Protein backbone atom coordinates (compact mmCIF):
# COMPACT_ATOMS: atom_id res chain seq x y z
CA UNK A 1 0.00 0.00 0.00
CA UNK A 2 1.27 3.48 -0.65
CA UNK A 3 2.20 5.60 2.30
CA UNK A 4 3.06 9.26 2.26
CA UNK A 5 6.54 9.16 3.70
CA UNK A 6 9.42 6.65 3.89
CA UNK A 7 8.73 6.35 7.58
CA UNK A 8 5.50 4.39 7.22
CA UNK A 9 7.11 2.12 4.76
CA UNK A 10 8.19 -1.15 6.00
CA UNK A 11 10.74 -2.98 3.94
CA UNK A 12 8.02 -5.17 2.40
CA UNK A 13 5.58 -2.23 1.99
CA UNK A 14 8.35 -0.43 0.27
CA UNK A 15 9.06 -3.44 -1.94
CA UNK A 16 5.33 -3.45 -2.66
CA UNK A 17 5.74 0.08 -4.07
CA UNK A 18 8.91 -1.02 -5.79
CA UNK A 19 7.04 -3.88 -7.42
CA UNK A 20 4.39 -1.48 -8.58
CA UNK A 21 7.14 0.77 -9.91
CA UNK A 22 8.56 -2.34 -11.63
CA UNK A 23 5.12 -3.02 -13.01
CA UNK A 24 4.43 0.46 -14.32
CA UNK A 25 8.00 0.78 -15.65
CA UNK A 26 7.89 -2.45 -17.66
CA UNK A 27 4.34 -1.68 -18.79
CA UNK A 28 5.52 1.85 -19.49
CA UNK A 29 2.62 3.85 -18.24
CA UNK A 30 2.66 7.50 -17.32
CA UNK A 31 0.12 8.53 -14.71
CA UNK A 32 1.04 6.14 -12.08
CA UNK A 33 4.49 5.55 -13.41
CA UNK A 34 5.22 9.18 -12.83
CA UNK A 35 3.54 9.05 -9.45
CA UNK A 36 5.55 6.22 -8.30
CA UNK A 37 8.76 7.45 -9.68
CA UNK A 38 8.36 10.75 -7.93
CA UNK A 39 6.83 9.23 -4.88
CA UNK A 40 9.76 6.94 -4.51
CA UNK A 41 12.33 9.67 -4.94
CA UNK A 42 10.47 12.05 -2.64
CA UNK A 43 10.30 9.54 0.20
CA UNK A 44 13.78 8.17 -0.22
CA UNK A 45 15.12 11.58 -1.21
CA UNK A 46 17.75 9.74 -3.10
CA UNK A 47 19.41 12.08 -5.70
CA UNK A 48 19.39 9.32 -8.11
CA UNK A 49 15.93 8.13 -7.11
CA UNK A 50 14.83 7.23 -10.42
CA UNK A 51 18.21 6.30 -11.66
CA UNK A 52 17.94 3.55 -9.05
CA UNK A 53 14.63 2.42 -10.52
CA UNK A 54 16.03 2.50 -13.94
CA UNK A 55 19.27 0.74 -13.05
CA UNK A 56 17.37 -1.84 -10.99
CA UNK A 57 15.45 -2.74 -14.13
CA UNK A 58 18.66 -3.02 -16.19
CA UNK A 59 20.38 -4.86 -13.33
CA UNK A 60 17.42 -7.24 -13.32
CA UNK A 61 17.53 -7.67 -17.07
CA UNK A 62 21.22 -8.53 -17.01
CA UNK A 63 21.10 -10.06 -13.51
CA UNK A 64 24.68 -10.55 -12.24
CA UNK A 65 24.24 -11.77 -8.68
CA UNK A 66 20.57 -11.24 -8.03
CA UNK A 67 20.92 -8.27 -5.66
CA UNK A 68 19.75 -5.03 -7.10
CA UNK A 69 18.17 -6.82 -9.96
CA UNK A 70 14.63 -6.45 -8.96
CA UNK A 71 12.28 -4.48 -6.71
CA UNK A 72 13.65 -6.01 -3.57
CA UNK A 73 17.03 -4.66 -4.45
CA UNK A 74 15.98 -1.08 -4.96
CA UNK A 75 14.99 -0.92 -1.31
CA UNK A 76 18.23 -2.51 -0.38
CA UNK A 77 20.09 0.33 -2.09
CA UNK A 78 17.90 2.91 -0.32
CA UNK A 79 18.37 1.45 3.17
CA UNK A 80 22.11 1.94 3.00
CA UNK A 81 21.88 5.48 1.65
CA UNK A 82 19.26 6.53 4.12
CA UNK A 83 21.31 5.06 6.97
CA UNK A 84 24.60 6.59 5.74
CA UNK A 85 22.97 9.97 5.25
CA UNK A 86 21.54 9.59 8.71
CA UNK A 87 18.00 9.82 7.59
CA UNK A 88 15.05 7.85 9.05
CA UNK A 89 14.39 5.00 6.72
CA UNK A 90 11.90 2.23 6.71
CA UNK A 91 9.80 1.21 9.56
CA UNK A 92 9.15 -2.18 10.89
CA UNK A 93 5.88 -3.92 10.44
Image (tube, rainbow, N blue to C red):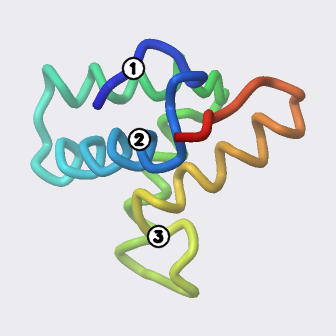
In the picture, measured across the screen, residue 41 lies left or right of residue 15, that is right
Q: Which residue is mark 1?
A: 3
Q: Is residue 11 above or below residue 55?
A: above
Q: CA distance from mark 3 to mark 1?
A: 24 Å
Query: Is disc 2 placed on a helix, strand or loop?
Result: helix
Q: Residue at x 77, y 41 (%)?
A: 81
Q: Quadrant of residue 44?
A: top right
Q: Nearer the viewer, residue 5 or 21?
A: 5
Label located before the other in sequence (3 or 2): 2
Q: Which mark is residue 52?
A: none
Q: CA distance from mark 1 to mark 2?
A: 9 Å
Q: Is residue 20 above or below residue 4?
A: below
- In the image, farthest residue toward the top: 4
Q: Which mark is residue 13?
A: 2
Label located before the other in sequence (3 or 1): 1
List x then y, in percent, for residue 87: 80, 24
List x then y, in percent, for residue 35: 28, 20
Query: Is disc 3 placed on a helix, strand or loop?
Result: loop
Q: CA distance from mark 3 to mark 2?
A: 18 Å
Split into 4 quadrants, where in the image is the N terminus?
top left
In the picture, measured across the screen, residue 79 lies left or right of residue 55, that is right
Tell me whether the residue at label 1 lies in contact with that at label 2, contact meaning CB atoms closer than 8 angstroms. Answer: yes
Query: Is disc 1 placed on a helix, strand or loop?
Result: loop
Q: Residue at x 24, y 43 (%)?
A: 20
Q: Which mark is residue 69?
A: 3
Label 2 Cα crowd, 10 Å radius (few <14 / some 14-19 / many 20+): some
Tell me whether the residue at label 3 lies in contact with that at label 2, contact meaning CB atoms closer than 8 angstroms. Answer: no
List x then y, in percent, for residue 78: 65, 43
Q: Is residue 74 above or below residue 4?
A: below
List x then y, in percent, for residue 53: 44, 46
Foreground tag (3 vs 1): 1
Label 3 Cα crowd, 10 Å radius (few <14 / some 14-19 / many 20+): many
Amino acid sequence: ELKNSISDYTEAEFVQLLKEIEKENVAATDDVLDVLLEHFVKITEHPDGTALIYEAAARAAANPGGDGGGPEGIVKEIKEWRAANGKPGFKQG
